[PDB]
Image (cartoon, rainbow, N blue to C red; front, side):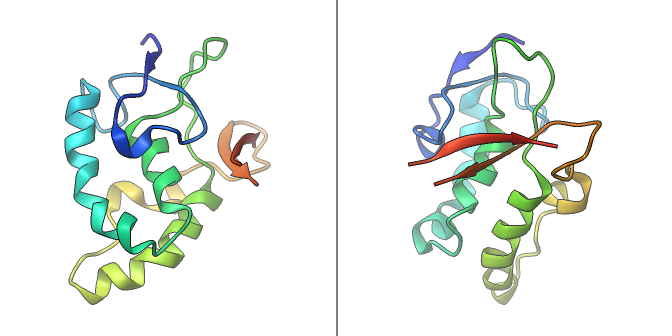
Length: 129
């Protein structure tokens, strides 16, 4: 579970530099993760949410920190903003918000027992409850 430089094009320049495999989807390589995340590219191009790119990468190329050796998922707020912007459009064309992307299964900000990832304005990563 060593850190490796992110090489998925969608996730290059996302605000953190390294990821790790396997991810929560059981993808063994970034090549495998990159292939599946490619499916979302029309929404990325349409730009239904400024949060979609960050959210997808936090799942497919989860952040890897040299001084923190546990999964650091995105905050529920990140999922909720991406779903707000893009899920109505996805539903219009027969796509449900993916089950593996259910927002209530992600840790809340300010939760004492977990750490989760968000960002603010250039993109600076913020760690939160």
